[PDB]
Amino acid sequence: EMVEANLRLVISIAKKYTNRGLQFLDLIQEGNIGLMKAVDKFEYRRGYKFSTYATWWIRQAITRSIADQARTIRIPVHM
DNA sequence: TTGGTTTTTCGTGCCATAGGTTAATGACTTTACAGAGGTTACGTTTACATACATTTGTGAATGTATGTACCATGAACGTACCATAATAGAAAGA
């Protein structure tokens, strides 16, 4: 029920990170994986909304996806 | 008067006495082959000192490793020229 009601937050934050690094369906899938990893470690006693906490995780997912291959060769993340 | 048998010399042919170059095996002698004996300058075997390598620990380069807590809620997010005709498909009236 969480993922079927928050796929659209993922696509809304994922359609602004499509700067021609790779085809964007992999970015949609990695955003869904980041949504899963943000739901798996979500707290209730904080009192804040879930989007601000999930934004950092989904940007980390999109960052590691765009820095995973990024070329035909392998370049590390720090480089 | 002329042809032919008979007979005797005479240079030529056969036999015998003399005397010399030159074949014989050898005895040569000279060259060649076969016998040992002292000396040379290597070739193989052996020990010993020092060297490039190769085998170890120790100080620096990167690299995945998990997370960051006001609010972020659907779209292509700029692609593209529009040739030509054999063979089927999903329906529409015959």
Image (cartoon, coloured by chain):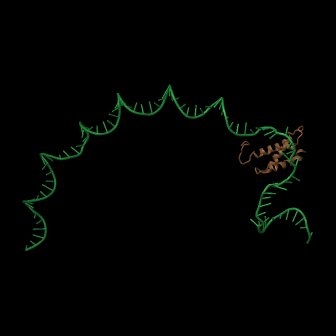
Q: Nearer the viewer, residue A53 or A39?
A: A53
Q: Position of residue A18 (x, y in %)?
A: 79, 50
What residue appears at the point 78 percent right and 45 percent down from the top-left corner? A63
Q: In terms of depth relative to the viewer, which is nearer, A6 or B55? A: A6
Q: Is residue A5 left or right of residue B30?
A: right
- Compared to residue B51, the image places residue A13 above or below, namely below
Examine the rendered structure and indicate whether residue B73 appears above or below residue B32. below
Residue A79 in which image quadrant:
top right
Residue nearest the viewer, comparing B34 with B72: B72
Say which residue appears at 83% left-offset and 48% top-offset: A13
Q: Quadrant of residue A33?
A: top right
Query: Quadrant location of residue B81?
Result: bottom right
Q: Residue B67 or B52: which is nearer the viewer? A: B67
Pinpoint residue A69: horizontal percent, then vertical percent.
74, 46
Answer left or right for B91 relative to B46: right
Which residue is located at x 82 percent, y 49 percent? A14
Image: A72 above or below B36: below
Image quadrant in which the N terminus of chain A is located: top right
Q: Is residue A60 above or below residue B58?
A: below
Q: Position of residue B57 (x, y in %)?
A: 66, 29
Q: How many marks?
A: 0
Colour brown belongs to chain: A
Q: Where residue B93 appears, x then y in whole percent?
A: 92, 70
The chain coloured green in the image: B
